[PDB]
Amino acid sequence: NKVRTVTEIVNSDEKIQKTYELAEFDLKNLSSLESYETLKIKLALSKYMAMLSTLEMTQPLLEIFRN
Amino acid sequence: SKDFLQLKGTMNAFYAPKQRILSILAVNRLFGATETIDFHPNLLVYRQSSPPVRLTGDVYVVDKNEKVFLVKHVFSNTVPAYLLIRGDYESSSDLKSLRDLNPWVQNTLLKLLIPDS
Picture 1: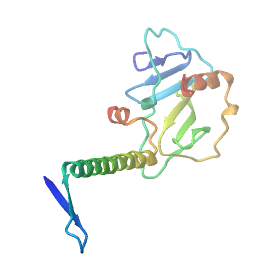
Picture 2: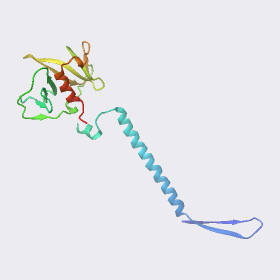
Picture 3: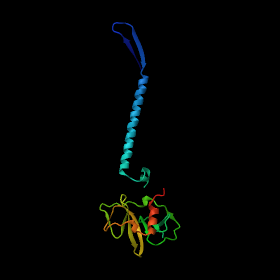
Picture 4: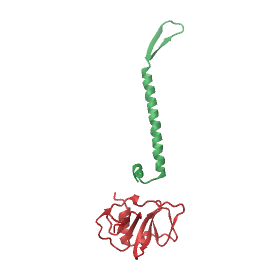
């Protein structure tokens, strides 16, 4: 939800209070997680494609399964 | 005959499905073909064999990577020709360069092998 912080000097009583809405950090976290997961999945898919290429079959995948 | 079909774009090449064989007449033309079949790699089904199948007579290498070979073959009725095969094969004698082949078979082979990009 939200939080707030208070700054104050030890010898003084004049304090400054600020408020933060956590939604911004929530957006940051969600975007980071989404990007990380997308990168992982794309990496795995590329690795799979690459090993299949390593097998070095001339035809494409669908043609292979059709033959 | 109905046992095979003439390959499109070839005057001396035909394919027998039941036998899964691609044949090229050495010096003879085909005739009467009302139908033709487009060439396709699937036709050269790779022969599986735990020990390489031995071959005799004249043998030529088409694609070492794909185990594609051309074997001289004469039909028992004495019809010279060559069989294009793909699979685990080995030659009893020394393999021979394709340049040894006649221009007729060579032209047919070029048509059949080089993709028409």
